[PDB]
Length: 116
Length: 127
Length: 116
Image 1 (tube, one colour):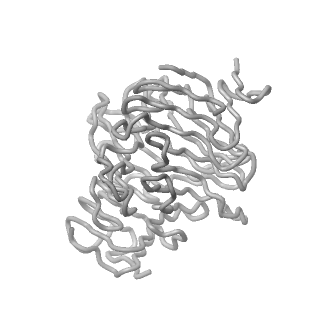
Image 2 (cartoon, chains in turn blue, orange, cyan):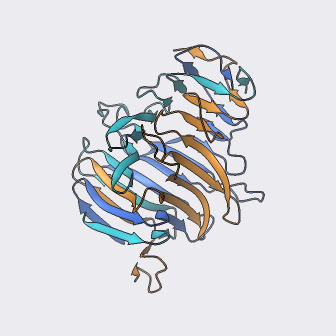
């Protein structure tokens, strides 16, 4: 690639004296900046800002964590956080509550939330 | 100075431009990339931008390290259309591991400020 | 450290002209690619693909957010996302529900999930 670093353990270190470290940017709103984790150069997970249309009011460009199968093919977004609302979706592409889960929910201490 | 890779006009200490796989860091043991800071009050950050405007960041904050693993908590921040912070969508407390959603100071293993939706029912299953 | 960058501000910017960005890769299935956050070069947090073995059917290599103590020693996995199922664990390295929490749960608005 443009930059290819090889090492053992600590491959690269980016040191900030303020707020910074690694910026991942794209040249257009339709291109998704991504941090991609691979093993033996096969996709396993990524965290990226997706291409959901930026329609105003801070909508679009939501944060997604994608999982990939053993061959590197997408299995979908396990987490989607919407930028306009902050709503946190688990197995839910369109979260509609501050936490929104599609499927089952397990809690080791009881069946209810504590009113905080 | 500044080092550009693919740009003759770099704007940070290192500035790399590519198409698709811009940079690949390969480790021959468990490991990878480190984001570090020169002092405890400086915040190592992973920042995502589009067209060089902030959108999201995952960073270690400057909550003070007062002992017993206090301070330096993780936060996932969202940013508005102009690139200004909208706040921490997620805050994870380092000392306790408590996971806050829209909650700056989580006090439960999961702590949500706002609403909660579950497709299958209104109760958690006791695990 | 093969590459060591220090800056005021952003430190390092990686710009993609298509969907893509930064790849953290390993040379073997048992070498875990990691993004490690340090202060003064002491571990504080990481996001990494974990050591669960890839035994087939997308098992193993789950995504973890780890928290470290003030000396840099591992304190725990705050979050683990299962690759084969997408299940989201909080304080649970082997989640068995779409959201699985070990410990307590607090909700500011009430005791129940809304049925979505």
